[PDB]
Amino acid sequence: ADFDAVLKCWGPVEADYTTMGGLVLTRLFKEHPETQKLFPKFAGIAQADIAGNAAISAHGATVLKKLGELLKAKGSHAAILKPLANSHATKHKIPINNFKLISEVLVKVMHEKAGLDAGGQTALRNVMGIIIADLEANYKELGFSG
Ligand code: HEM
């Protein structure tokens, strides 16, 4: 019931996927600059110009919309997830650790801007842990590391 809880807390996010999408990626890039290089479209953008950047916010919106779809599946996510693992391993070539980095940023932003309290934070970290474990498994099956 870490999923039942999370969906309760998701409302404020789904109310504005574009602003929160922009916040989450800004924070990722400011706190973990090495991750900006993994986005050819965004690499080399001045740190001063990230916040409020429309192309970043638009991609952030896509990120969150897809995470929303994953959360709403409440653990029966294989059919949504596998395609995400497919693209991220073979087209974008993203090492698993980066998924841990954005999960921790999402928790921090939701805590600060969307009312995610200590309890919600725990439930979300548990859900994210499940998803990343599943992503790891799919990466394995694709032969894209360990
Ligand atoms: C839970 C986390 C994430 C979700 C839900 C997600 C979702 C998506 C979606 C829906 C797309 C577009 C469709 C596709 O190509 O699969 C995509 C593209 C992409 N993702 Fe992710 N992503 C996640 C994490 C990351 C991370 C951590 C990075 C690198 C640090 C990353 C790098 C990329 C890149 C480079 C693209 C292509 C952008 C483009 O060409 O416009 N993703 N992501």
Image (tube, helix red, strand yellow):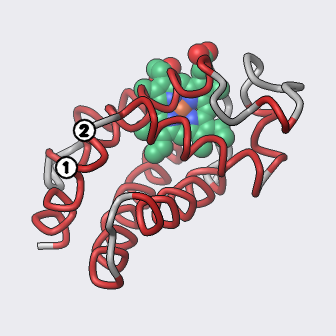
Discs 2, 1 touching: Cβ within 8 Å:
yes
| Quarter of the figure with residue 80 | top left
Quadrant location, ligand no. 1:
top right
Residue 127: x, y in percent?
Answer: 31, 65
Q: Nearer the viewer, residue 5 or 89?
A: 5
Left/right of residue 41 with respect to residue 88 in the rendered view: right
Disc 2 marks a residue whose amino acid type is: Ala
Give the image location of residue 89, x and y in percent.
Answer: 59, 32
Identify residue for label 2.
15
Q: Position of residue 95 (x, y in %)?
A: 68, 46
Q: Is residue 109 left or right of residue 101?
A: left
- From this view, report whether residue 78 is shown above or below residue 124: above
- Residue 11 circle label: 1
Find residue 49 and report its horizontal and vertical position in percent: 79, 29
* Local crowd size for mark 1, using a 10 Å CA cut-off: few (<14), some (14–19), many (≥20): few
Judged from the image, the secondary structure of the residue bearing numbered disc 2 is: loop
